Length: 221
Length: 201
Ligand SMILES: NS(=O)(=O)c1nnc(NS(=O)(=O)c2ccccc2)s1
Ligand SMILES: NS(=O)(=O)c1nnc(NS(=O)(=O)c2ccccc2)s1
Ligand SMILES: [Cl-]
Ligand SMILES: [Cl-]
Ligand SMILES: [Zn+2]
Ligand SMILES: [Zn+2]
Image 1 (tube, helix red, strand yellow):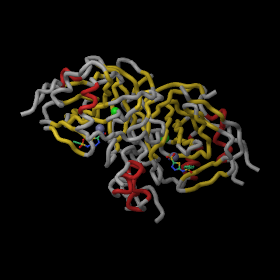
Image 2 (image 1 turned 30 degrees about the vertical axis):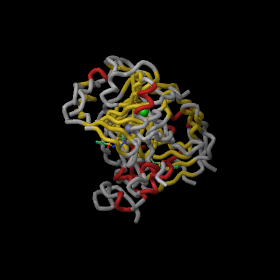
Image 3 (image 1 turned 45 degrees about the vertical axis):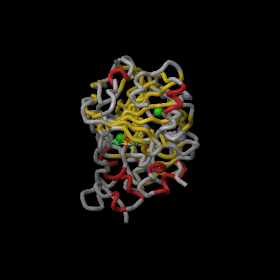
Image 4 (image 1 turned 180 degrees about the vertical axis):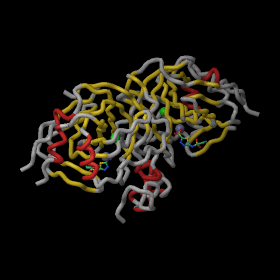
């Protein structure tokens, strides 16, 4: 009944076989992740993050995750989408014109009506990322998460309609995928891939039906 | 006992009318503007089957006319009508719309000067399909669904903002071929549809 990553029937091809809830994992017409390659060039995104000690930092459902009480928000089209948690994927699930990065993080948001907004940004092999240390460094009175420092000040982003990359693979997801990589050290990566128990948590690319993707740019602060 | 809030209970086949997260029609009210950039091309031709079905008038033909979008070939199948127009562009009322089923192309009709392109509808007539669409068009494009059951998702919708013109008698006359009953699906919940704005010849 427990779902997972690799080849065996408890696999990617067969999420839908695992539960009737995960049917859309097969039946859905806007499933993510995908390889983002045809888009239109052309913003109404606004940021309310604050430095916060997590509510919980825990590995759950195959992934490392940090949760927060809802003090942090994202504003889209005059609507506020509140941050509930932040989790990690390795390697990066969404591909930008065939572009994997060893790590990505996903900011999960919901609005008043319960509509979903999710932010993805990839990581590069590079200098050490300090914003990572409160998550790994510390397990227990929790340590600050640099939410205001986490994201680039300036970003190019892709916006499109897709789906959840983990069950129930729910559609109607507002996806924002930042083109700008953040940078992480190599042992932070090894340690964190080992803390995600070193089994790749990258959902294979989903079918593409000429999704409308836009590319844009914003200030996050 | 055969209604819209209820399409999903009529069949298990039709649940996506309710479970769907990208259902049409909806209100086109937030959009993105963009340049002369696209791929959309029209190979319509004057073409000479007509029948009333499922609340709707529809004319279908042989696979002779097709459209180019992003390098994919889409063959036109039929044209059918909705009154009043289902999709809304900035709350834009419209007495009549038409759906070019291929990717579906919608364009509304307004009361005014008679549309000569409508009369062959009101051995079949030549239809001036080549005369039917504006040579210059502005449209809204996004991914949506069929507006009638089974409400299939994955539909490349293109909504041209430019109105065509209908007489009142023409306006009245085919509602009767639709049995004077409105075949307009209410606006569905929207989950931040990405809409792009552009224009084509
Ligand atoms: N990979 S993905 O699409 O961002 C996610 N898949 N499942 C998730 N579960 S979750 O982040 O804990 C969550 C939390 C609140 C509402 C909905 C989902 S996020
Ligand atoms: N109103 S809408 O979105 O254009 C449609 N909804 N259902 C349709 N079915 S149909 O017109 O009979 C048809 C005809 C040929 C191929 C596919 C579908 S069209
Ligand atoms: Cl990602
Ligand atoms: Cl319409
Ligand atoms: Zn995720
Ligand atoms: Zn229609």
